[PDB]
Image (cartoon, rainbow, N blue to C red; front, side, top):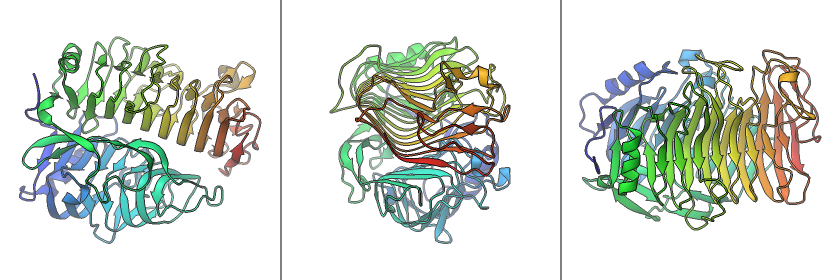
Amino acid sequence: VVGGGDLGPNVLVFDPSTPDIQGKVDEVFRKQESNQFGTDRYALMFKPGTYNDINAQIGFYTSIAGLGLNPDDTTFNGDVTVDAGWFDGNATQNFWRSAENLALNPVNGTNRWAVSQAAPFRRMHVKGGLNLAPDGYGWASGGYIADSKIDGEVGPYSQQQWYTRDSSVGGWGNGVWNMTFSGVEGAPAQSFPEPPYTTLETTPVSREKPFLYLDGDDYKVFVPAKRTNARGTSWGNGTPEGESLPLDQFYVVKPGATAETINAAVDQGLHLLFTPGVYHVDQPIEIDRANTVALGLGLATIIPDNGVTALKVGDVDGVKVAGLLVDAGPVNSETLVEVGSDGASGDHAANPTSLQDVFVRIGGAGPGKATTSIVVNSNDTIIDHTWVWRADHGEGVGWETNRADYGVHVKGDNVLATGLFVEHFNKYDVQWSGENGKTIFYQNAKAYDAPDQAAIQNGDIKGYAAYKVDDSVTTHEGWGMGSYCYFNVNPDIRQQHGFQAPVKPGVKFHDLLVVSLGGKGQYEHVINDIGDPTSGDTTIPSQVVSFP
């Protein structure tokens, strides 16, 4: 109706005194570990304090977070663990979960976080090691760490790629295909391809994700200020910049609340808190009020009915969308997420809009279709961790059954993407038409299910680039960026390149690679006509170190 009130039956809130925390977190996990396409959603929230005897195992659609003004305010003598036991060592489907704002003192000196995509690890203090591979040496496809600090060494082991920003680590064990770092103290030296480390001193701009906390015995949302030249944690010394907003200024969205009503809230001047669950909407969610926070908990999910655009953000400063999944419905939406309206040359440099831990799925948990997933019109927008994913397995998958032509389409100027994961689109996964774009870390996989060469011919080109820049663009820069193929339906296919871009002095790429998995199809080149083809069946990347 208003601000505040309860968080709903999916927001489980603990203090040190709570009867059997362990057996409880294991209760949620037993429900959620193999629950890949289920509709249950959980947020586990912990008041400031010290928690003994806890191995908090995190399954699908589970978020865990501390409630302290600082991470060290909520301390586990114990672990927040992701492993792969349900896929027999294979961490490759460990999606859609999250940990934030906790200190961990892990049980054997290491904490195990063996995740793949859409599994953010933010604002975490690990007083030990961090192993990013499940128990195994099994295959893994992560991942994202921000504003964290790992007193010890990070161990990616069998992880294919990884992005870390604005953190400190006590060590970094290895790189496989693409480990990228920006603003990370203790990050290994720039060395791609050998090892494949892409290392930037600082992050051009970042703004830490808002989060729910107890300002004493009062719930508020902390809303971090941005930094230029971010390096290291925002909190280390942490009395940093930002505003604390009472929960009583948030529409606490649940039940099967509606779209008229959610949009009524923003207009009446409220922020949005999506408690964990699944929201239809037969109409779009609309945020055209400057500095509106729309914060999800427990992988809160929006499904658009009727072919509408789930979320539309108008031409305003400061909007902070965080921690939402948008799951396409049966009717093809032209767009799923629009950031800014169309032809809008207004600049937003002081107080840009951001999408953080915004995930998109097309198919998998049933039929879904969308023409474009995310369109970014707003100049100066920050895209800080997104996974935009056309499903390659689960219910409702198929070259027409869940066709999604376009992943992300950036038309705004001065847009920054940090931790960009986009996979399986029928045409261009990513297209960049705006000026002066920057991407730090890209991971792509091409659609597995294109039937034949003729189905993916792109004028004079075989296949659509995983990342296209329009030939008129004069400035662009990308760092640490890979495209992989697995043409299973037709391993005779050729993909002409991962990347396409005009040859111009202001259009620069660093540390590119393409990869064929098991000789299933091949790349002709890396970028335009530069870089070798892939060949053999051995899964050996082909890399370009700088371009043009």
